[PDB]
Image: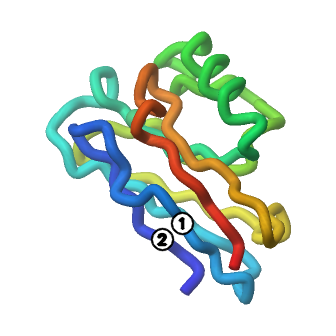
Amino acid sequence: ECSVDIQGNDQMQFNTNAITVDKSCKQFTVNLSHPGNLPKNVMGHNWVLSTAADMQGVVTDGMASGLDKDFLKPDDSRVIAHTKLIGSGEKDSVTFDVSKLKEGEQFMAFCTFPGHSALMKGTLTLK
Ligand SMILES: [Cu+2]
């Protein structure tokens, strides 16, 4: 129980707004998929993890980075883990070390495609 399957869809939502990572896990894996019909340049989604304090800067700088950079500032030290940006019918996975998390803190998981984090934002918590 050290992975989660996340979908981002044409309605600009992930399937979850709260991810729990079992603290017995040494690594955690997010398997993102896009069950919609819309292409990456219209309704692209990524899955990006940061602290709550860093989310807004990652989102804003991501928009400024452009589609060709997956709407994610390259080499952003604030990004704990992230997938690539995907469109309809694609999938992407990322694994990260659970040592990057700590109990008692709600981390933020979000998409940086412009506008999406109005809905595509939620918490991740080690329990
Ligand atoms: Cu998105």
Q: Residues within 10 Å of mark 2 (few under 14, many from 20)?
A: some
Residue placed farthest to the front in the image?
104
CB within 8 Å, label 2 to label 1: yes
Q: Secondary structure at mark 2?
A: strand
Q: Residues within 10 Å of mark 1 (few under 14, many from 20)?
A: some
Q: Quarter for ligand 1? A: top left
Mark drawn on residue 4: 2
Residue 67: x, y in percent? 47, 18
Q: Is residue 57 left or right of residue 88?
A: right
Q: Is residue 122 left or right of residue 28?
A: left
Q: Is residue 93 above or below residue 3?
A: above
Q: Which residue is mark 1?
A: 19
Q: Is residue 24 above or below residue 14?
A: below
Which residue does the image show at 42% across and 56% down from the upper left?
Answer: 32
As measured in the structure, the alpha-carbon distance from the residue carrying label 2 to the one carrying label 1 is 8 Å
Residue 10: x, y in percent? 22, 38
Which residue does the image show at 45% across and 26% down from the upper left?
Answer: 113
Q: Earlier in the sequence, mark 2 or mark 1?
A: 2
Question: Looking at the image, is mark 2 or mark 1 nearer the viewer?
Answer: 1
Query: Label 1 amino acid?
Result: Ile
Which quarter of the rendered picture does the N terminus lie within?
Answer: bottom right
